[PDB]
């Protein structure tokens, strides 16, 4: 009576092969979100956004992105605004939202902008040679650092989808 | 991305679909000039006649008219003790006086309305929308329009002229793009209201503040970012005709002050619900324009710009 | 300026998801459902047993994409509604304790529902493979339209075992 | 899960670690009884003596003591007009009258404290903590107790308080007092672990008495504790608690206190009058963690996980 499942015919194709075009489609939406952050908080810059987009394309194409966060961080803790994108498999109808809906008017005085990436299991299992070939075009290289915390809560407010894969966006929200 | 839609794309779109074609604007101006010439001729023969001047007063006179213009705005200055001080009576008075000065037209062509008197011609062009202004000899053609509201069409037209002189073409074009967007929001969104004059004054304030109007996507983004981040709570005053001291205290939520009348707040009527609508709409449009900047294909770029400018936009 | 997660901090090299790991995740979902029961009257202990059973079957087979349990008012989820999304374990791996169901929310006219979306592996499996994997199901679900959400989603817990994660989002009243 | 830790496990942990063993409780009662009988005999010889009675008044008297009981509570009723008004003089006066009545005790063994007077037993004994009650002969030994929180005068009746508790124990023999003791044990652990956490034992007892009156089942300890934690979390301590054992609820006057748990003897004495919002927040967060843990332990797949969840509630003394 009250137990339901998603309609069988509503499921999208489940046999999609993720390509560079799908990578660029997701990365363009992140770039948009970053440009929206810039308009209301001053960072990141257009040139940094361009490099973030290139980086995202390379990691998505290779399947090496687990999760990446961009935004303002105090001490070792993210504050609002901070946008986090977790890679996953496309579900159901495959929600592919428009980018945007950055909250304006938040206090960021003490923090500086940062980004932090977590690589996927496929990356950790890859050979050194596989990594070198897949990541040749990286615009910059990242250095290990202690995982940051969150000063606030996470709101899951967008999903970007392409080629059988999804990016799930959570936005850090201040306690109020 | 910009490869698919850029400033020149928007500029072409504005001419094709947004702006009032010059040919049509010329026709409308000649229509008004015809009435004005008749009034001057009649006034010359009868100096005691109440109707002292007819001035084109709206978007057409300011060069901010959209393709969708449906009438020609003019003000008629009315003097003397005979003219009533009630709008129904004053509009009746205006209509009778218009009938006297236009003996070639039939009486039925001149029809009064709630806030104005309309002169219509059957099957030959747009109607002329005439707003009465009570005149008592104040300088700069200052007059009053249920209390009396002081105004000067020449000074209002002068204000816009100075901004158009500061940024030729670009200022009037951005004003028209923003009005065109505001019209699309009103049909798409129920509680949405955005007076054309407020749009004009907000953009004039941005121009005064140094915003660059020569790139239409970025100029629109400055407009949209201003609305979102100030939340329409920043008072807008110009010092063209008076110092900012003159405003005094106001209890109004939105304060966008008539550059001709320091006592008139154009946004006086706007509520918090009206503001939330503008803000939400401006956020959506800013989200779409920045999405179009990075969109990987032409099709997505057009679809994002259609959030701002509607189905007429095709890139 | 640009950092990533320390190599050492990542998970163990080889993890094969088993029914043990499935039961570890499902027990935590069951706990969450009993917390909901204590502050909102539903679902019952007997229903929770069936939900846990079902979750173990689908988890074991890798067929779970997402499942929601909670109250619906009109035709949308309201607070409380708990949503669990299957994914791969990332980084150090967060295996939280279950719980943190807010009390006091309005569920006056509301009824309890659960809604499941299967994974892409379910959809790519043959009907023969599906029937052997879903042999031990305690009940069967019927197709329905995905309901809306009245509020926002808070991502507030992660349960992890055997190289896989369940990410929990909680519906919240607009405030 | 329940196969790893169930009601019987909790009942056995209670006997092993939580409850005060009877042999110790008998020793403590005899300590108190020895002083009470000595006062009765002295007062019989000296009818004008200020100290009129000594009544065991705390957890030991109520059958709710923990193994960690650190002293023996008794109330001493003080009549006459020789007692000074101020707290320091009163406790000094009580110390003096106690030495007069127990001349065998070394005077140094009678020590005024902040709101009470300690009587120390040299050999193999806990101290006796004597709380003054100003008494004027009213029925049921009604008098003005000195609060052990801030020294305020509380008009109440310790005998009627003991009656109140005994009626709840009659309504659930063994189980009511056992659940009280489990909740006090938890609260004691929270006070060590959490900074702003206070939870007066008498308040715990009154909250549980209300749940019992309301029909909560105390015969299964995991569920009875869950009812207690659930109540704390869902009311947030903002539901006024009133009993009608001794007066009708109409006698309660409106109060502005944040937490209102009204003395069953005295309708204007709010037992929780001192609890602040930070206190309440500490209690609620703790009750939520405790409830989450107990229900986690209900489904946990292994004994080790189950024990770890219960140790969030009862600490490292709990081993399954
Ligand atoms: N606020 C209060 N008002 C009246 N009596 C109290 C209060 N606090 C404690 N008592 C008395 O002290 C006894 C023991 O308290 P407790 O040490 O919390 O178990 C209770 O049974 C009451 O008789
Ligand atoms: Cl016009
Ligand atoms: Cl005691
Ligand atoms: Mg008009
Ligand atoms: Mg004591």
Image (tube, coloured by chain):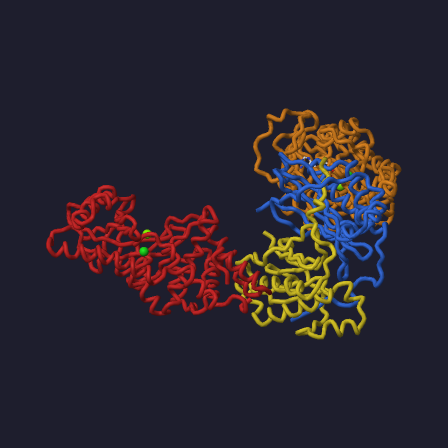
Chain colours: A yellow, B red, C blue, D orange
Query: Observer-nearest residue: A60 or D243?
Result: A60
> Which quarter of the figure is the N terminus of chain B placed in?
bottom right
Residue C129 screen position, x and y as percent: 84, 49
- Count up the numbered dots: 0
Q: Residue at x 73, y 70 (%)?
A: A144
Q: Quadrant of residue C142?
A: top right
Is residue A74 something that shows in the picture? no
User: Left or right: where does residue B215 sit relative to residue D84?
Assistant: left
Where is D151 relative to A150, above or below?
A: above
Residue B66 screen position, x and y as percent: 38, 58
User: Left or right: where does residue D156 sit relative to residue C56?
Assistant: left
Where is B46 relative to D269, above or below?
A: below
Residue C20 screen position, x and y as percent: 86, 50
Residue D63 screen position, x and y as percent: 80, 34
Query: Observer-nearest residue: B219 or A142?
Result: B219
Ligand 5 image-quadrant field: top right
Where is A1 relative to A119, above or below?
A: above
Where is B89 relative to A84, above or below?
A: above
Q: Residue at x 87, y 47 (%)?
A: D303
Is residue C17 something that shows in the picture? yes
Q: Quadrant of residue D117?
A: top right
Query: Observer-nearest residue: C64 or D228?
Result: C64
Q: Residue furthest front?
A: B123
């Amino acid at each position: 009576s009250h137990h339901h499942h998603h309609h069988e015919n509503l499921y999208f194709q489940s046999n999609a092969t993720f390509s560079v075009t799908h990578a660029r489609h997701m990365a363009a939406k992140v770039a948009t979100d970053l440009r929206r952050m810039q308009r209301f908080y001053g960072y990141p810059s257009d040139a940094d956004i361009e490099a973030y987009e290139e980086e995202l394309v390379v990691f998505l194409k290779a399947g090496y992105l687990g999760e990446v966060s961009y935004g303002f961080q105090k001490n070792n803790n993210w504050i609002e605004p901070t946008l986090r994108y977790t890679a996953g498999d496309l579900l159901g109808s495959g929600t592919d939202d428009d980018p945007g809906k950055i909250r304006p008017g938040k206090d960021v005085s003490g923090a500086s902008f940062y980004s932090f990436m977590t690589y996927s299991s496929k990356y950790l299992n890859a050979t050194q040679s596989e990594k070198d070939t897949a990541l040749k075009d990286l615009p910059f290289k990242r250095v290990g650092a202690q995982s940051p915390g969150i000063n606030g809560y996470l709101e899951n407010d967008k999903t970007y989808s392409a080629g059988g894969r999804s990016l799930t966006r959570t936005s850090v929200r201040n306690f109020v | 991305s910009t490869e698919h839609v850029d400033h020149k794309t928007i500029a072409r779109f504005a001419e094709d679909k947004v702006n009032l074609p010059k040919v049509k604007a010329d026709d409308f101006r000649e229509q008004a000039k015809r009435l004005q010439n008749k009034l001057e001729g009649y006034l010359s023969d009868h100096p005691d006649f109440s109707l002292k001047r007819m001035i084109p007063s709206g978007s057409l006179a300011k060069g901010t008219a959209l393709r969708s213009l449906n009438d020609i705005d003019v003000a008629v200055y009315i003097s003397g003790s005979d003219a009533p001080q009630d709008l129904r009576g004053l509009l009746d008075y205006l209509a009778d006086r218009l009938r006297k000065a236009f003996p070639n037209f039939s009486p039925d062509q001149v029809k009064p309305q709630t806030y104005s008197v309309t002169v219509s011609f059957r099957g030959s062009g747009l109607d002329v929308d005439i707003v009465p202004v009570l005149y008592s000899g104040l300088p700069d053609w200052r007059g009053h329009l249920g209390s009396f509201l002081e105004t000067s069409i020449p000074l209002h037209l002068d204000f816009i002229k100075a901004r158009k002189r500061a940024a030729p073409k670009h200022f009037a074009q951005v004003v028209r793009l923003a009005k065109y967007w505001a019209r699309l929001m009103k049909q798409e969104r129920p509680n949405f209201r955005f007076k054309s004059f407020m749009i004009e004054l907000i953009l004039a304030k941005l121009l005064d503040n140094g915003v660059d109007f020569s790139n239409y996507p970025e100029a629109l983004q400055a407009f949209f970012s201003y609305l979102v981040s100030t939340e329409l709570r920043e008072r807008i005053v110009f010092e063209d005709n008076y110092p900012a001291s003159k405003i005094g205290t106001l209890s109004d939520l939105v304060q966008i002050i008539d550059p001709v009348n320091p006592v008139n707040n154009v946004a006086r009527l706007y509520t918090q619900s009206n503001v939330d609508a503008i803000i939400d709409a401006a956020m959506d449009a800013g989200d779409a324009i920045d999405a179009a900047f990075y969109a990987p294909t032409k099709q997505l770029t057009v679809t994002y710009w259609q959030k701002v400018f509607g189905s007429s936009f095709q890139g």
